[PDB]
Image (cartoon, rainbow, N blue to C red; front, side, top):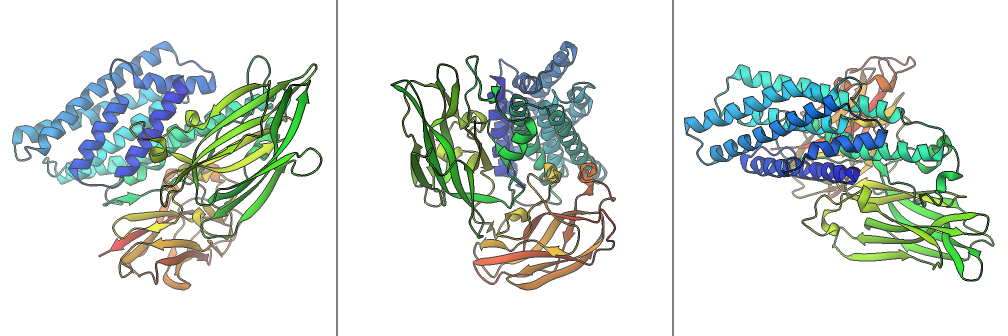
Length: 589
């Protein structure tokens, strides 16, 4: 199926780029293009047709033949031109002073840029912007990486300062435009899928997960292709949670959603309230026995107790389903502290009785690793069933590893974050966090560190808005003066290293901001509003700005804290709001 393939491609691509973010050296860049070209143009078959098939399947619309045929021809020709640009980069890298060679690489680059300019409108044909969105996101991505080579290599190839500035100004304009198109059509696509029943909810949530992976996640990285803003290696984190399909049996003999709560009931029950970025620490699963006749029985997950924890914060525990009484015949406790569960294999069971069906999960295998010491283990829930219908749900179909060139315990893209649940039918949903989002809030001496403020140990939760479609996760919002939580940090050596800080934000008001390090203020200033007073849905890429300080500071110790405070709003009128996205720590030498 094209969906699995497309998601596999998109996850792999974001993993590769995340590993090269902000690198200015030609060797890494040649190596990157080599990988990108292999993935996007494997030969004998259009990898771009797979992107189209994906979104057509998710939304149940067909791209017109004319529009499909043209985009496919243009994308195949762009691929041929990309091979020539790669070969021209390889021949430049080893004969840099040759004039024939510099003319060649410059010429190939200008041919690509020119083709991108001509072809981008083919990936957003009117009436087809959604089914063509994953194509559009991947092509946009390529175009912005190309413009970044102009920034790193342009002078070397003999571009004038005027040409180089034009390329840079276009890249800024295009980051904005491509980001906006993605977020917008992602929202429209998902909204067109809003329904009233549980089957529709499965569809809506599948588009949400797949397009976050295929569209939103790569778009989130677009700003870091700006080499003036990110002139060195950068550590980005995607903090959003994605949810896999509900773990219930589906088919012609009976689906769990044949008799289940409404769309709205599922959205408000399967999906967690807004919360600070967290990690699972413990799960208890409560088991019931349903039986039919003498030898057929289903022992299934009828409720659970789950504990999680923000980085360096308190542990919270919630309960779901049935967790006491005569129905509970067994319990199992699973300690998950420090464990990345990289794969779940679940058995969604059905017990067929004379006049009814009983749905429920009979078995879950959790494959886990400790990212500290790389110690691996399996956790198995299997109380034991017999004579049942079953479906195997393998999380790596929806959340694949970033490569198959290594074991999945090295290349996994996501970890299990949480479990929600409904009863009758007894159906759990698994949520997951991205590998890029670390456990420790590590600060690097030699990189720009990005730290989303949602990774605080405590304090205010995100508000109910989707501004994080632009950010790769939830911002923290203020309608009046307040602080982020204490963000707990692990500082890499040397502790004598100076850092300055800039904060990514959006506000309808001017405000006072300071940075509190280890309990004491190290930076304070006033910052200006970046957006009009509008609902969050109207915010665009250009409404995000930096609060940047030049005055550096050092951390006190290896385990230090950071905290952002906002104050003295220029207006308290209804709509007055500061969103805080992330802090970036920049080593000062």
